[PDB]
Image (cartoon, grey):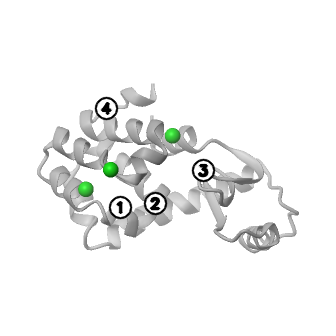
């Protein structure tokens, strides 16, 4: 299992504009288009992001190209962030993927908000980190996804995804 396979499971793949869990216009593999209530705003974002007039529909290749960009951006973002980098550097491979997953879903700022969880991860206190992360809006809004990511942090294995 790898980061792409993991996120493909968590996010799914849709080739037409759709609304995410929070009601936002998205496409492909979890690619947020706009927070705006406007479908026209969504279509405009999409055309800009793809480089062609898509009329709210993309190909599989196009979805995978956005996904590659998004994963790359998440990893580089982690590496540039003063609060996230040291945690990433301290973790083993599997757990690194768990962090990239979180950043992909909530952004760098959001993840950096989990102060205590990050501290616990850095100290290798797996159960404590898991318990802290569960006390969040994130966990209450998307529990199944959260539990899979938390388990990954907890065990350092891909069990939750197999
Ligand atoms: Cl926390
Ligand atoms: Cl809570
Ligand atoms: Cl969920």
Residue position marked by numbered label 4 in the rendering: 157
- Quarter-of-image position of residue 118: bottom left
Q: Which residue is mark 3?
A: 21
Task: In the rendered view, tell whether residue 26 sits above or below residue 50.
Answer: above
The residue that appears at 57% across and 42% down in the rendered structure is: 8
Q: Which residue is mark 2?
A: 106
**Taking 112 as reference, is 9 above or below it?**
above
Q: Nearer the viewer, mark 2 or mark 4?
A: 2
Earlier-in-chain disc, 3 versus 2: 3
Q: Give the residue displayed 57% in from the left and 63% down from the top.
A: 69
Query: Tag 4 or tag 2, which sits nearer the N-term?
Result: 2
Disc 1 versus disc 4: nearer the observer: 1
The 10 Å Cα crowd at callout 1, few under 14, some 14 to 19, many 20 or more, is many
Q: Nearer the viewer, residue 63 or 39?
A: 39
- Quadrant for residue 70, please give it: bottom right
Measure the C-alpha gap from mark 1 to mark 3.
18 Å
Q: Secondary structure at mark 3?
A: loop
User: In the rendered image, which residue does mark 1 sit on?
Assistant: 111
User: Depth-wise, is mark 3 or mark 4 nearer the camera?
Assistant: 3
Disc 2 and disc 4: Cα gap in Å?
22 Å
Among numbered discs 1 and 4, the one appearing first in the sequence: 1
């Amino acid at each position: 299992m790898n980061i792409f396979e993991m996120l493909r499971i968590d996010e799914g793949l849709r080739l037409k504009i759709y609304k995410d869990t929070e009601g936002y216009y998205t496409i492909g593999i979890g690619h947020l288009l706009t927070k705006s209530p406007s479908l026209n705003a969504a279509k405009s974002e999409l055309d800009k992001a793809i480089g062609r007039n898509c009329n709210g529909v993309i190909t599989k290749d196009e979805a995978e190209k956005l996904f590659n960009q998004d994963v790359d951006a998440a990893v580089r973002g982690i590496l540039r962030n003063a609060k996230l980098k040291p945690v990433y550097d301290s973790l083993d491979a599997v757990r690194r993927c768990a962090l990239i997953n979180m950043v992909f879903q909530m952004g760098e700022t959001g993840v950096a908000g989990f102060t205590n969880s990050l501290r616990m991860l850095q100290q290798k206190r797996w159960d404590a980190a898991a318990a802290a992360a569960a006390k969040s809006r994130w966990y209450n809004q998307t529990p199944n996804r959260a539990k899979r990511v938390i388990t990954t942090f907890r065990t350092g294995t891909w069990d939750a995804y197999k």
